[PDB]
Image (cartoon, rainbow, N blue to C red; front, side, top):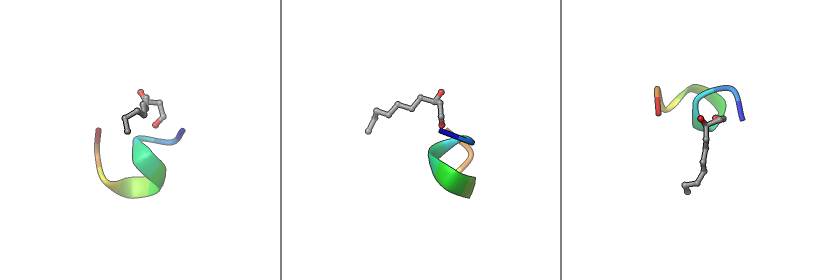
Length: 9
Ligand SMILES: *C(=O)C[C@H](O)CCCCCCC
């Protein structure tokens, strides 16, 4: 999901 929407996971 986009790396947790931007969390980078
Ligand atoms: C989107 O961000 C793809 C990621 O690789 C997987 C996210 C998994 C969410 C489950 C952990 C809360």
